Image (cartoon, coloured by chain):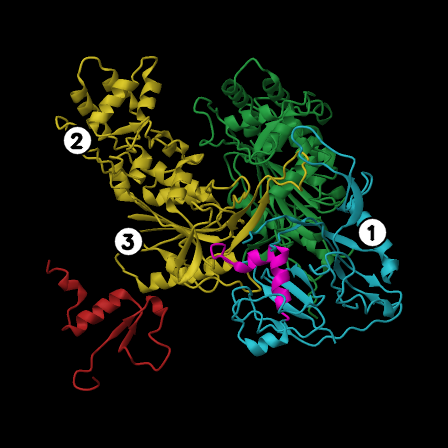
Chain colours: A cyan, B green, C yellow, D red
Amino acid sequence: MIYLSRLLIDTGGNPDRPRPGRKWLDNIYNVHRRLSMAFPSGLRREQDPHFLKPFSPNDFQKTPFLFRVDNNIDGNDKRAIIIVQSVLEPDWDYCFQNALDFLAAPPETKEYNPEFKAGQLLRFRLRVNASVRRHIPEMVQQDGQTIETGKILHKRVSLTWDASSTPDQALADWLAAKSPKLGFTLQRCELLQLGWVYGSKPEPWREHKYNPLRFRAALLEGVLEVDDPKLFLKTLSSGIGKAKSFGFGLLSVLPI
Amino acid sequence: MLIEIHMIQNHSPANLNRDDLGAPKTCYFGGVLRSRISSQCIKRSIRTSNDFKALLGGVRTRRLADLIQQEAGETECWKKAQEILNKCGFKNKDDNTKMLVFMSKDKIKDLARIVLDNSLGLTEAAQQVANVIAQATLAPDIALCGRMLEPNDKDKDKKVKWSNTTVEAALQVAHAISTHIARPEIDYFVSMFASACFYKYFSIDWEQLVKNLKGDTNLAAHTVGAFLLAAAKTNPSGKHNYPDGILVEFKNSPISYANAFVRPVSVVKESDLVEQSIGQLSNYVNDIRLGYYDEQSPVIGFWFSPNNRYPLGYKHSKLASRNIGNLNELVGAVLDYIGGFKWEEVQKSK
Amino acid sequence: MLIEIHMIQNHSPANLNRDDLGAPKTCYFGGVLRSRISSQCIKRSIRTSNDFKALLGGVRTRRLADLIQQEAGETECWKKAQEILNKCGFKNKDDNTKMLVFMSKDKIKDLARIVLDNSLGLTEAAQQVANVIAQATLAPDIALCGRMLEPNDKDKDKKVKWSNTTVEAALQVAHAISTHIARPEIDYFVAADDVPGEDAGAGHIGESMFASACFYKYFSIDWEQLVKNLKGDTNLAAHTVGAFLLAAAKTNPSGKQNSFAAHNYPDGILVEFKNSPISYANAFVRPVSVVKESDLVEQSIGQLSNYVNDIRLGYYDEQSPVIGFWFSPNNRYPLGYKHSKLASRNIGNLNELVGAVLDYIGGFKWEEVQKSKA
Amino acid sequence: YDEQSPVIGFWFSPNNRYPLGYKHSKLASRNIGNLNELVGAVLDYIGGFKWEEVQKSK
């Protein structure tokens, strides 16, 4: 009995009109915060039922929520799509009661229920950031000449491939390697979005700071096969990759 | 004269352009929505392809001081070059400048030579550097894509002057438009994807290419042949997927056959999308042949298909002079109409 | 008798005319937003065209003294010409006079003779320059687009008089408008720094604006005023009319056309001759909506046919006959698709359309009209 | 006013492109589809002046 709905964003029309939704999607933390507030704590509704106070996340409750940023249902209208799921009841009249300019159509929600079998075909779209934890030589200053010390910095490098390998079967081999651990097996998958995803974060007289959030996103699509139905119920609403809370874990439950 | 190439190609949506939101680019043409490939996407995809890699004589750099520190070897010519570039006009926000410099791969050595020389002051160094990066034009990529380089004046010395830092383009590439209405993705609110039929229109001015290349002729012929080969043998980002049909004509005025697809080619059968589009093109071409092209200078054209699979003459109209089936033969057939221009002897020029 | 050109032309996605902020020119017509192409841009594209290059005897200059130096020879005449133009009524605050002089015609040699004449002082030389600027009076683009200049009276010492300058142009161009809702789109462009860097690398991030539209263009040439402005020379008048028709039929504004190459040609040309000017933009008060089994161009031509038939039937005077020539590319879209033969003739090619226009004008042909280059 | 003076009106549209209201008719005594006929009807109601011999007045 999972909670699947649709938020609908314009991303089009007259360029002269300032569209706050367009800058709302052009950052991770904005959509993250707005969908995180979309499950408010119950005592706030009893206290302020009108969404008319300076909020605080300590008053809010915390759940491993997750979304999906897509676009382009055609038919002579370019439009952008937000697909959200989590485990608690969301509210959309509470969330966007002052943000009617954010959307291009009123949101809609129905009841959806997923079922899985053994050795059954599926169709899926996932998004996982290309993340490989590596020891790197540090490279700072860069004032005319390179300067390094013996310290090896620890971070997650974006995925790279050898010069005799195209990106396509490299990410196919990544998905093939990650399949038997998570609980499925595929025969082929198609790469259709490899790119860079940028964002920024504020944090606590104090100031505010801007740092470029960095994620090597990978959105794929097409034809899934399963090995056991019991290895998929714990995958939905939790995520399979990294940047889990940032909207990188929705299992597209479309059996066809 | 003006060379115009109209090609019909099949492009899968996994190998296309995107906007800031990850959406494939779309445009409203004829009142209906079409999939769009931007002109700059095709321009850079042709630029960075394997076929055009021998003529990639241009660079577009915000970090020119790094290119200064690539051949001298001595460590202490990076700050001097930075102050020289600041005195020329390009701001120093980071290690890169604030403006984009369109340069060629033979004056970088001269720039390093001027920077490492210590017999002159900063102002004369800036003047010599401006004389260097205002005539850095002898590059086929510079000739095709054009150039508009321009400095900042509030943070520039009053004595250093700038020459004509503007090279007008010779390549007019239209935005590629899907003939059909763009196929909607499977709405998930309930080998893999069919490739879209794209119409591409490239216009090259021979005269503008030869004054942009300072009168050098065989380099321009090699540029045109390599551009045609790269246009028919590329896929923007990622990745044979040959084009379905190429019409090359040579006239003195530009003409766009995009209005062939004002009416969408709405075909339910997926295999009939391509040849019907070719038929539609022929219809419009015939109209443009008759309603606009009479007397003065008749236009000749060459048609190409993969082993002559899809003809465009409607089996009786001779609107294309010859239908050939080899892409290299098409390059040879469009090279020798401009005069001589053997393709086998043109590759020995940069 | 008034010559009227109406054109329906569908353009590919482009940005032909832009504002200071890069937005394409819009207009609010019929209560809805339409794509607008300015009449000045069409007039320049006609004037700076291949066919209308033999009649470009009109220059608009602030750098007049440098043309005087250019055709004056090796003699230095910039200072004396600058002083003469200063006391003539053209102030100079920099190396450019703040007065756009449409003296236009190629009798710069006469101004050269007055400037280098070392026999008369500055005052009567200024008078002899002033009476030769006022008698421009010629070249087809001044007959099409007149003059306005009125010297300067905070300067120009009162020993020098001035004559008439206004030419009272005979060409009226409406701003080209789209027949449907304007659909403006955002395009994303990056610079893509070539050399490797520490970051992902893009030298420039920004937005561009474009649109695609089906434009209706309206041109009106007052034949009698255009003959009077040329001071006779009816052959030059016919060459002007034919060159205008051909150039407007095949030319487009050059704005952003290197990356948005949309050199599309018109699909409908209605040429009508009558004593009173009529604009059919009221045909497209309601926007053209796409129907599944037809195209936008055919619908626009149908709406034009309906409104033109209604206008001719509702404003019919027996003493003023109204005719029409309808041209489509190889008769692609007939005008009277429903019931009527609105035009006197449907014509498949541009050349005999021009020939028939000249046949109505005076019976002249396109061949012998070429001689009056001027 | 609905009696005494009845207010005679004429409605002209180009080839009757726009009817004067799609509701109940007889708002205008004559829906004329031509301008010269409207001039003739106006001059006829003014007292029977044909358009031809009023032109000879000046």
Label 3 element class: loop
- Residue C226, compared with residue A30, is above or below; it is above
Check if residue C51 falls in the magenta segment: no
- Give the spatial CA distance, label 2 vs label 1: 85 Å
Check if residue A30 falls in the magenta segment: yes
Q: Are marks 2 and 1 on the same chain?
A: no
Q: Quick check: can you spot residue B336?
A: no
- Residue B231, compared with residue B212, is above or below; it is below
Name the residue carrying label 3: C276
Disc nearest the viewer among 2 and 1: 1
Q: Which image quadrant for residue B144?
A: top right
Q: Chain of mark 2?
A: C
Classify 10 Å Cα crowding around label 3: few (below 14), some (14-19), many (20 and above). few
The residues colored magenta run: A13-39
Label 1 element class: helix
Q: Is residue D35 left or right of residue B85?
A: left
Between A6 and B96, the one nearer to me in the picture: B96
Q: Which mark is residue C162?
A: 2
- Give the spatial CA distance, label 3 vs label 1: 75 Å
